[PDB]
Image 1 (tube, rainbow, N blue to C red):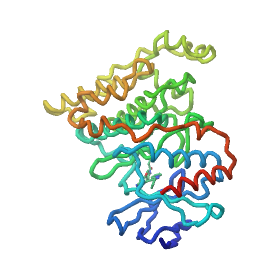
Image 2 (image 1 turned 60 degrees about the vertical axis):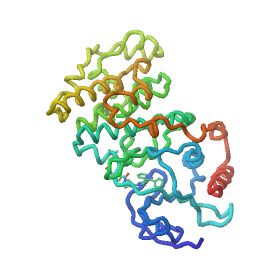
Image 3 (image 1 turned 30 degrees about the horizontal axis):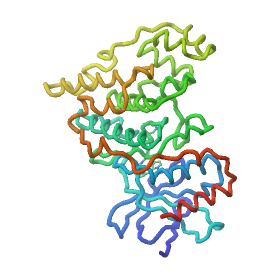
Image 4 (image 1 turned 90 degrees about the vertical axis):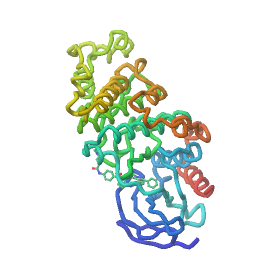
Length: 355
Ligand SMILES: *[C@H](CC(=O)Nc1ccc(C(=O)N2CC[C@H](Nc3nccc(-c4c(-c5ccccc5)nn5ccccc45)n3)C2)cc1)CN(C)C
């Protein structure tokens, strides 16, 4: 297993099977290169994490995502072809390389391509399949947005990361690009506490964006985000508001009361194909599902299991993908403990050596 070094902005030491390294982006966790794997005969993406153990946030993210790849195994979630380090001992250990099949684009790039119903409904289906698989493994993503999701030109899709640990003191973030509130569920903006269907809200916002071509709830701060939500969906019920913490409830109950816009005006026929018997049906189904995902009160928001059975999605439904439990449930207790930087180094190195 001899290595080759190639400077690509920084410097990439990789097994020689990986040829033609080309930069294609920069992740929160490090530099991504495209490459060709001459052993497998396929294009791959190669990501280098430099000293993931140096920073605590980077350590918990590197460690939990290494472990989670042993818990999940699903076509719509990142799975790794290879994990390696070029350093030969624990204490010269610095760099972890992750290898997966090369994806063509991120979802943030497909937003402006005005997809038809067949492609929109297939992307939605795959998102729901991956999320159901993540939930079954004990993972609520909590930070799904267009940039967390990559696609190939054949419209296949993978959720790229495992989201936000509950014990993340970093609120709701990590940065390839500009941190935004656009996809965060209202219960999260309001400080309420969250359940799994926070991920359904995010998927609704993404689906709305690919229908409309623009961001559905484009708040410019925490306060403006809530306003953009109630302006379009209506002020939620008194029960929901009463359950807020008094200071939040005081502010929220004092806003202008909005009635909400019917989804037939929010998502009218003219932003959909809608131009045939078949497309009028699909448009009605798409809008009905949107009206069940984009629901402020999480107790009335559709679940992933329910969304997966929706008529808009049936053309794609395949139990081999939609009813596919994960190899293991994640044991989070080990990620929540303190761990010094040198403990993280050992923990990460061990996982790297398990490959
Ligand atoms: C707007 C979007 C924008 O302006 N620019 C932009 C957005 C996304 C991308 C991108 O994500 N791409 C293009 C090719 C890349 N292919 C690919 N394939 C597989 C994996 C990755 C990848 C990995 C990774 C993980 C594990 C092993 C190997 C690789 N990690 N990351 C992190 C970030 C991005 C990709 C990636 N990539 C996908 C390019 C340009 C958004 N704005 C509105 C917020």
